[PDB]
Length: 130
Image (tube, rainbow, N blue to C red; front, side, top):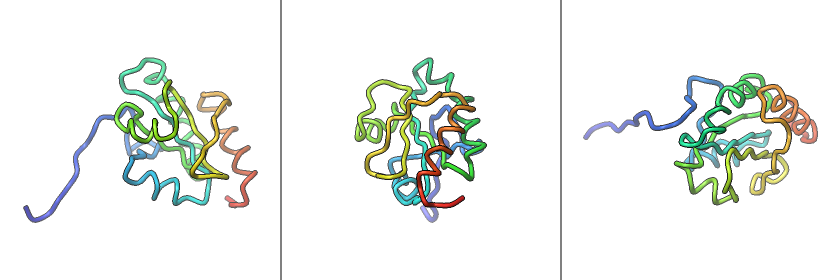
């Protein structure tokens, strides 16, 4: 052809929302290349509890939109990203800050509210103002 393009793929979330669609092609240029804080959640469009974390996760992405980059990786699809880290049971949230190569196991609340408080608490720890 002359010009290439892309199409809409499977995913409980959407670029429209505040959640950034993280993929095994930009995950690095999105998170690894983000001195700031990043919150990646490994969900599954085939699981239950996961599909119920769409609104909860999105909410946090809206508030932490400018605070903490809250993305989303389809463990089912990006099986490479999830496993590459150690994701076996979703939902599985991961915090990126100190070591972009080795995130922290998010234990805080998985609610749009809790997430907001979690992302912040972590942000402070980092020098990256904003």
